[PDB]
Amino acid sequence: NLALNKTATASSIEGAGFEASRAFDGSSTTRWASAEGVDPQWIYVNLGSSQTVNRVKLNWEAAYASSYTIQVSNDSGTPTNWTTVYTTTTGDGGIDDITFTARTAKYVRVHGTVRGTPYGYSLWEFEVYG
Image (cartoon, rainbow, N blue to C red):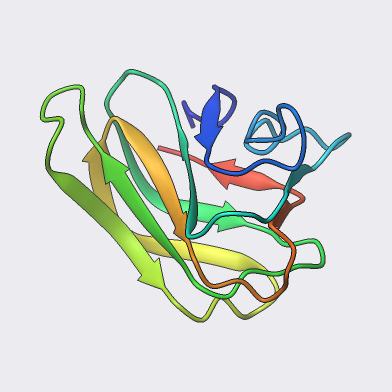
């Protein structure tokens, strides 16, 4: 869990800094919220180092998401090729749990185009480990 606190970049935001600062921060005080606008929408984290990923935890408040994918890019070595870990289009089952192969990359990115509501994004807790 190296990118489980660092700074992340989100295409859309609910306000001024709601990108992913308090999203992967695991801050129980405040939750991560995003405002709808331009789609599709995606969010990735920044670290600068090469880390592996396979398990990802995602929660929803009220505006649960419909479809979503988990990809990763390793620009630290080859800023061109893209590697994925898991892909889903259902996003249904209360808690969002993603468990697949352990891909190696620099930063992780989350794709999202299909939503289960007009609301941008709603996250209460985010867990990401190597």
